[PDB]
Image (cartoon, coloured by chain):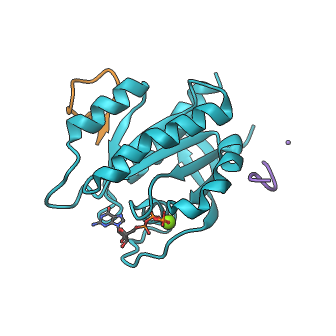
Chain colours: A cyan, B orange, C purple
Amino acid sequence: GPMTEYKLVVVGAGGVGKSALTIQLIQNHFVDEYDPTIEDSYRKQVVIDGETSLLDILDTAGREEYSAMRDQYMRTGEGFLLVFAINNSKSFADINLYREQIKRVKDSDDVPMVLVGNKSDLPTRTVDTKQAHELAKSYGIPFIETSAKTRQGVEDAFYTLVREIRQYRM
Amino acid sequence: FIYWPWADLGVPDCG
Amino acid sequence: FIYWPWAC
Ligand SMILES: Nc1nc2c(ncn2[C@@H]2O[C@H](COP(=O)(O)OP(=O)(O)OP(=O)(O)O)[C@@H](O)[C@H]2O)c(=O)[nH]1
Ligand SMILES: [Mg+2]
């Protein structure tokens, strides 16, 4: 019709940059302070490849103590950004737990997902680009290197996810 | 910044 | 268009 709608969920360990990526997409601003999330939601209209879309984006908690809220957003969400920080190897190892829970909750092996390696503006890193690309290939999904600080790859991560859901629906 | 599942390992597509 | 997408 006139508009399409996509339910996107941003997931990953605490402090990797989920809120900063979302806020850079929606407000065109970089958040320097770390305000740990419980659960925030945004709705933003965009045009992706000529399609007017309303993106409903849920910005989730990385802190372990909010893990009981995962089942609900996993059932609802249509696509997931699996975010890790390239200087946080623990957050990269935690990606598998999120992908496994999504798979179990949605009872599906083809749920739209994108692996995101954030903080690409840093001068050093502990997770190699090849290591993250290798994991994303094992999942059959794209991997995007982003910087919420410089805005590099931010639209690429969210729009690649929208394109995957659009294709999934067909 | 995009590394597709079919791309050479660590090679991004910028087109 | 959906009025409450997390709850045509
Ligand atoms: N250098 C750099 N710092 C970043 C980047 N993205 C986020 N940060 C910083 O990392 C910290 C945490 O970012 P948030 O986006 O709040 O982290 P989060 O993943 O939402 O965390 P939780 O809500 O607790 O799960 C903040 O100080 C951000 O400014 C980035 O691309 N580059
Ligand atoms: Mg947050």
Give the residue at x 64% y 21%: A170
The percent position of residue A145, horizontal first and vertical second, equals 30, 47
- Figure check: A51 above or below A120: above
Q: Residue furthest bottom?
A: A33
User: How many discs mark residues in the rendered view?
Assistant: 0
Q: Nearer the viewer, residue A79 or A95?
A: A95
Give the residue at x 35% y 37%: A143
Q: Is residue A46 visible?
A: yes
Position of the C terminus of chain B by quadrant: top left
Position of the N terminus of chain B by quadrant: top left
Q: Is residue A153 visible?
A: no
- Figure check: A78 above or below B8: below
Give the residue at x 27% y 52%: A86
Give the residue at x 23% y 46%: A127
Quarter location, residue A75:
top right
The percent position of residue A91, horizontal first and vertical second, equals 37, 52
- Figure check: A56 above or below A132: below
The percent position of residue A134, horizontal first and vertical second, equals 28, 29
The percent position of residue A42, horizontal first and vertical second, equals 63, 62
Q: Nearer the viewer, residue A13 or A112?
A: A13
Q: Nearer the viewer, residue C5 or A133?
A: A133
Q: In the image, A9: left or right of A138?
A: right
Quarter location, residue A61:
bottom right
Q: Residue furthest left?
A: A123
Q: Residue furthest front?
A: A65
Q: Nearer the viewer, residue A83 or B11?
A: A83
